[PDB]
Length: 248
Length: 248
Ligand code: HEM
Ligand code: HEM
Ligand SMILES: O=C1O[C@H]([C@@H](O)CO)C(O)=C1O
Ligand SMILES: O=C1O[C@H]([C@@H](O)CO)C(O)=C1O
Ligand SMILES: [K+]
Ligand SMILES: [K+]
Image 1: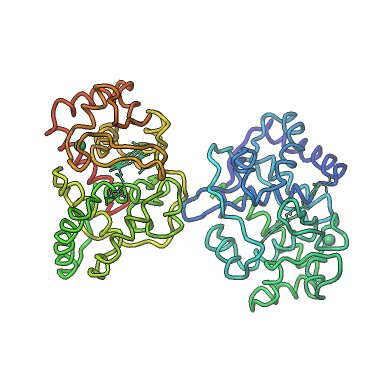
Image 2 (image 1 turned 90 degrees about the horizontal axis):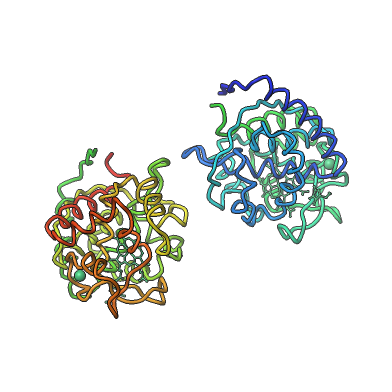
């Protein structure tokens, strides 16, 4: 239920130019997964009951980067600082979410609609709102549902974001890619999740929780059979996540 | 601006009986300062922008007792558990605030009006909202003013709560009483604050901040000259603090 704010023509021109520069930079640096993870951890702190947190640029604060769930995301902030400085008119909030949208696009994923106008806010949210990889469906619903206000369909679709990238034992402690093609955005996360553990590939307990839940599991089966349907629901869910607490 | 909830006659009878039992117990155990500090740290987590936190019984949770600002308050919770069990109808929130009101009364202080009907809530607030003793007036206003929504007069009056009790090097790290009579509720905190450091008595940086601020300092002078005026403003401020986020 969104009402997007008006931004000047110069702001809109800067979005379009930054989008292109982000494509080139993210593709060349091979950091699309990290950038997706930065945008998601930015937005995923939203609490709908208090309207605190969410995608309002606070993740660049050292206080929020120190959160253990954000281990490694200081690399992302640093990687983007030279480009952000070329687009001073843009908020950090818009810039990081635009980077997440581009991360998905440049790895072959759906084109997530983007609307500008997030304002940078000065206080990071409390630590502890991001999901815990060792937990299961109840915990997923607590975080995405009770806090962020996303649907069970969004949970499954957004979990397929793991179709790009890898864990790092020096960041979370988990290690390895979810897929055999970690810079390619496709439905492979779901086909691997269904096939069992393969050697070399990662499954978190929070991934496996999707297989045993009666609402999540049919979605997993849908996305593994129908990549177009995964792309549609993913684009819906990403857009919602990127706009949590914004333009309501 | 309060609208107090209706409670049954049995609840009201239990308040009155617990008030008496609290007087006897707190007087005998010599723990009025700790009990005041428990009630204040319960209520002082209130944030008026989000309506989170405040005096709703969450301080008995191990998660909130672990907060470093609450070092030692597990002693208080434990001390009160046998009495609370004699009054099962009462919420923990009402019981702890009633204990704070009695702590003030039984050490000779003003009779703070008490209204029942706080409901126990299940989530403790985030850590870090209670004031920092090494900081000054700006920090006091951030905490009491911007979060809790109390006035500068309340800040000074409520700081005179230090007229009873002591710091402990194994809890905060500070050590000693503010006053020569730490179980007597009087204006002595302000007369000591004005006289300078005396040997054996404690002044926190947050106490000393009251002397250098142009709004706080006249209040300090008022309370040190006029204990009746301290008692009046204290009773006002304590009642407000004990009712933050309650019955609005
Ligand atoms: C469902 C609950 C989730 C849990 C428990 C979880 C947990 C994790 C963990 C532990 C890592 C490894 C971090 C590291 O060690 O480098 C990770 C990586 C990643 N996460 Fe999630 N995550 C969840 C949901 C999401 C969502 C909703 C998105 C985006 C839509 C996402 C995108 C990513 C990406 C792209 C990576 C790889 C990052 C890289 O390669 O640097 N995750 N996640
Ligand atoms: C103004 C900002 C405040 C700061 C920075 C502060 C800080 C502290 C500290 C560090 C201690 C010592 C804890 C220990 O080591 O045992 C303490 C004790 C105490 N505080 Fe405060 N406090 C403040 C306000 C308040 C308020 C508003 C009240 C109640 C109205 C209060 C009541 C007490 C009492 C009664 C004690 C003594 C506790 C005991 O003897 O066990 N304080 N405070
Ligand atoms: O997605 C990522 O990009 C870098 C690296 O893989 C390529 O630069 C990294 O640290 C990430 O987790
Ligand atoms: O106010 C207090 O009561 C006890 C003790 O002084 C008397 O029991 C203590 O640990 C407190 O800080
Ligand atoms: K993939
Ligand atoms: K005293």
